[PDB]
Amino acid sequence: SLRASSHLNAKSVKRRGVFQKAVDAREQRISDKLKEDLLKQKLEDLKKKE
Amino acid sequence: RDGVTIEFSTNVKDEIVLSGNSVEDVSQNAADLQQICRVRNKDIRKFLDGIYVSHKGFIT
Amino acid sequence: PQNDYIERHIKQHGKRLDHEERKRKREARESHKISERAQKLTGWKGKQFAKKRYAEKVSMRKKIKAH
Amino acid sequence: SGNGAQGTKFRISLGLPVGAIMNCADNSGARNLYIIAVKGSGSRLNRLPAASLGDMVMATVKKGKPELRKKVMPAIVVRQAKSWRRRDGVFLYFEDNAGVIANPKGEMKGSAITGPVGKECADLWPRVASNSGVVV
Amino acid sequence: MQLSWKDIPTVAPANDLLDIVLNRTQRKTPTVIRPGFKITRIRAFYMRKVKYTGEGFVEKFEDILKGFPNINDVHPFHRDLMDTLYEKNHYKISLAAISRAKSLVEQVARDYVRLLKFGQSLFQCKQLKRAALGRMATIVKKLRDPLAYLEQVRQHIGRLPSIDPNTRTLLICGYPNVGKSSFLRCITKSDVDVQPYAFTTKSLYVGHFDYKYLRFQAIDTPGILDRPTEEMNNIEMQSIYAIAHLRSCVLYFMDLSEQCGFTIEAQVKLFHSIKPLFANKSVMVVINKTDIIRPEDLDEERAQLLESVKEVPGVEIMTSSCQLEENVMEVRNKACEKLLASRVAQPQARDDVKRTPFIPESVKNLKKYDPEDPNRRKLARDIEAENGGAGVFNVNLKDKYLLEDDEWKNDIMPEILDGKNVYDFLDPEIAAKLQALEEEEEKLENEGFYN
Amino acid sequence: MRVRKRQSRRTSTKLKEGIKKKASAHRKKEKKMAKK
Amino acid sequence: APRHGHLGFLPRKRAASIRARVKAFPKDDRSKPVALTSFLGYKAGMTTIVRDLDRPGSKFHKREVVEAVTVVDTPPVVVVGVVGYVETPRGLRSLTTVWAEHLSDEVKRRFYKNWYKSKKKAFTKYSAKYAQDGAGIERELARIKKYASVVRVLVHTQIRKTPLAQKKAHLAEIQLNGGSISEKVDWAREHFEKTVAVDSVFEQNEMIDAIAVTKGHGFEGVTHRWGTKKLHVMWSVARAGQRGYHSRTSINHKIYRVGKGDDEANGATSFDRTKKTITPMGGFVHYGEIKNDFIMVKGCIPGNRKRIVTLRKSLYTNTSRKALEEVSLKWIDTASKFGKGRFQTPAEKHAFMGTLKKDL
RNA sequence: GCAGUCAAGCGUUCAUAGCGACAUUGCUUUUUGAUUCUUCGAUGUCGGCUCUUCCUAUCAUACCGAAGCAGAAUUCGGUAAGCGUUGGAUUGUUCACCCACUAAUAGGGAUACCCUACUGAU
RNA sequence: AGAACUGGCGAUGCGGGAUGAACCGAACGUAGAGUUAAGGUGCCGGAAUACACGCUCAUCAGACACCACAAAAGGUGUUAGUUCAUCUAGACAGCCGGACGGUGGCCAUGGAAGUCGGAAUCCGCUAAGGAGUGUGUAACAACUCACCGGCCGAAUGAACUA
């Protein structure tokens, strides 16, 4: 079944394992790009400011 | 659970010790594990393995 | 295989660590459980159970009638 | 699917309904088959049960040795006559429908084979892979 | 079927049987009928119901009867085992009675369904249905008695040890309080009790062992008392019929010691009583518990008994005990050889030179694998296991072999261009060929050919 | 879950005033049997 | 037997907007920085892909296998405003919007419906409210900093940067999955009139959800609507009606590529080493070119070509291996789908054909 | 079914004027599975599909108890209707009954533009 | 369905029965006031969430006579009882001890000693102790209550009824 308690909690411990850690590092990885995009557009704005 | 302590047994082979102040808490915890180590699909008349209680006494 | 061997395994390994306590407790509970049953069982098992309990009663009635 | 069939089967197109004549690629001299049955069947109303490459059937021999005729025995499909898709990317097909005979366990009835067998059945059935002279 | 009977799940009592069948037929078949429905439907209803009840009954009884072995002409050995143990007459008459009851079920079925097409009304037809069901119930409660016997034999039949008389076996027999259980447990993979009382082994206990790449089974006796020499209890008759029927060797396990329920003079006369059952059995006697006694000092009359055992053609004394391994395996080996006693191309080398086999030095130089060593070769399934399981681990197919350099072993083959992918191009001297065409274009560029 | 049907206590007329109308006739039968 | 239909998408009517509207988001995690929870672009066509396979245990482990993908135009996406939302015992409540002091002709052309006759007066009082101090703005902003347990941001696309010509911008709201709502709106306020990549939300080895509106097919009756057989009333008796243009949601979608417009040779694996963008010969089929970022995801999204979709980053912490496998492309087919395409580049066309009458 | 026994109780009061609870005994077509190919006036009009939903007294799929359960699988029973129950062979006929697959191949019930309902649309 | 007396219907409205071919009440000019019938007074609904004694807690409670009823019975749910019994000369619960001989009673058996089993089934001392309810050894063995006494002290048990 999809929604059996045994398969579910057996999947919850694994979700608490490697997968959520991969995602927690992925979100920092992508936060780096998400924040440096502002820096790229801001140095373009500096090229406008000069 | 809260207010219950656990001690792996000294100088008694294959033994575990519980200690606390709340009878209901310690007994519920003792019951949980012996349900979680419960055998299924099989004959307990031949298979033996399982955790049970030696006795239920005070600390003192 | 190997004619009767469960008893051999019993004497060599015991019945369980704790079986006798469960065995006592089952019969400690059965009094409450049987009446709780016969109040339950909507339809035809309140008939079969009732006939069973009646046969039990009349059998023990024959036993006390023995003397 | 049954016993002997090491590994799983991946989905392929389905060409062979029941009543579908095919060749017998064996070395017993048996010549043809007439499918009656499939093992590993789907369940649906009004369907015709399909067989395909890698699958295992029960079927007759309509022409061959008379001692084997008027008797039912299992078989494996070896040539499909319908287009399928191996994931290593290509579409393909053999020309003719053919199926060889074998015991229910998977062991080949005859000792040898004529003509090409698909990669799928070859990978699937080791006794096919041992008695077969050809691959594709 | 021969050598095992397990596909008989149980036989219930008559009351359990009828309760189960009647509950099944109340459940499955419909139960709701009014009077105002039509008479075709009302006849069909009770007809289907009684037919389904007969179906359930006969479907039970076929599993009963076909489950059982039909002992007549299956084996004289197992048939005699059943004769001593399982009350042959009760067995046959009970199964015959229930088969007769099956015929009675079919008869009442066919008679009632012959009637019921003329069903007219409820006070007739409902009572006809009850009448048929209670009649088959009357057969059921007529057939209560044998079923407990049938069940209790079925409990024991599945837990029998299984021995085919036609194969090589080793019929080891010893006295009560002889040490045969301890001896068997030492020699063989066998769980048999070692408390020294007489009737410790209760039936034909089996123990396996190996010799000369052959399987061998060890059949233990419960002990025997032949004091009438005609009649012995159901425990003792089993090994008697085994020694009668099993076409294999027999091993006598003698104990010439005080730790018995009887004297030593009883042992030799018991041997003499059982003498006629050694026809083709190639007997071999061995003395046990011998370290305490050391019978080299044994007295003249008892030694005369030892010689008086030895008139039969096949007989052999040995000495062993139940603390040493070498003598017990020796007697086991030569007993198997006694049982054996009772039981390619050339090249021509077509050549002048020899084709010697190639075995390089490294396969001999390497160490044979130790299952447990603190440090050893790692058996890389076990390397996989400690990082992920055995299904989830991806393995680098690179970085496991030799090359010019291991730095770029992880390098990606381009393997592809716009067209005509490179592995049809790839060889050495490609720069030499490039120069071989560089000179050609150097010719043709200056000749005005590309005008 | 799938909690099962509840059977009525509605008017639903057979029972009630016409059947033990007949059961008043059953009291008549009681009188008829009481003579014996 | 089964029923010749589902029952979940039962009121089979057309949706109200071609923008399939986000209904669900994964809740929050107030330990991280802010990560945008969605993005949106315009579907353009399909291609075929082969891919070497690190799938431990599977039959196709360490093999090449052909599969099939789609492609979507994913330009940078500019933020224009925010809204707050507060929990009630009714649900949620829009309590303030705030906009970003200068708005494109595109979104001004969205909110108007007959453009050229309009005077285009869309925010002329709002930009006047953006005074020397922005007093009312900060008033209606710090309110949201106080209230508004969860907050969204408005986006609009840059659709002029696509081969498509509609001139109009597709608004949306997007939820955040960071904490510190003050930090959320401060981040967004800094992002006012600033734009965002798609490799700054997504990356490879990822799963997404694809929510869109399907292709329409008009008023097709039972036999092709439900796949039902051919020779009072209940609502599940397989009666004819509108097909297509329903909203849907497709999940467990394995991305393979996060493309880039500036990156030449977007079609380049490590293997090809050919300077070709993924825009194949002939242009796309009813779509143009791909000179922007893009996504290459397997399966097939609901939609038709030159249709919008919305993206969500899989809404929970997946558990399957396939959600975590490591992708490696080997080859992009780059042939024209305007026919049985054979050739990747027109230079290859020249090379295999040779020179021709019109060539000289 | 019929006829007893056993007989909690009932009867202006009651064994014996008389009924009667539950078990038991009487064969009812054969004590050693040898079989017996027994379909013996089926007297009615439905039969067979397209195809929807509901009931459970569940045939598998869930979780459980006990059973000589050493295991595998099976024998019963309990909560369980969430999801599923086939392709052929044979008669105007539903009566009758096989082959093989699959996890199983459970039982039941419920002209037509006109207004309504249903599917869709402003 | 076979008979006979009487009544209601049919020709006959009206209040109540939630609504009605058969029930309760009551037979009519048009109108006003008053008072009642049968049925009812949480709200729909005019009329009290009146007072008083009890009972009952239903995993479909029950809510009206004849206008959807079943018994027999089962029930360690609750109440009121009847009749038998024991009891500060110590009631019952609970703890401890005692719980002996010929005896391992008779054949039965290969082994069967209080209990695989059939027959019998007693007597001494006894406060009490059976040729011995269950536990169980191949046998024995060991343990318990039923049978008694101690330590605590007030009521309590059995059967039957509704």
Image (spheres, coloured by chain):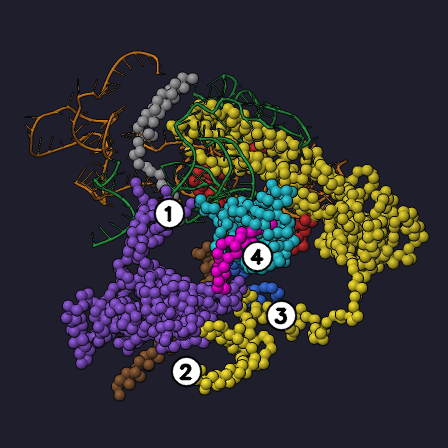
Chain colours: A brown, B blue, C red, D cyan, E yellow, G purple, H green, I orange
Q: CA distance from mark 3 to mark 2?
A: 69 Å
In the rendered structure, the residue with mark 3 lies on which chain?
E
Instruction: Name the N-terminal-most of marks 3 and 2.
Output: 3
Secondary structure beneath dot 1 equals loop
Tell me: G8 left or right of A1.
Answer: left
CB-based contact (under 8 Å), mark 3 and mark 1: no
User: In the image, which is nearer the foreground, mark 3 or mark 1?
Assistant: 1
Q: CA distance from mark 2 to mark 4?
A: 57 Å
Residue at which label 3 appears: E379
Residue at which label 4 appears: D117
Indicate whether G86 appears above or below G274: above
User: In the image, which is nearer the foreground, mark 3 or mark 2?
Assistant: 2
Q: Residue E196 at what x, y percent from top left? A: 76, 52
**Front residue (pair G41, G176):** G41
Q: Residue at x 62, y 30 (%)?
A: E100
Q: Residue E229 at what x, y percent from top left? A: 83, 39
Residue at which label 2 appears: E451
Residue D85 magenta: yes
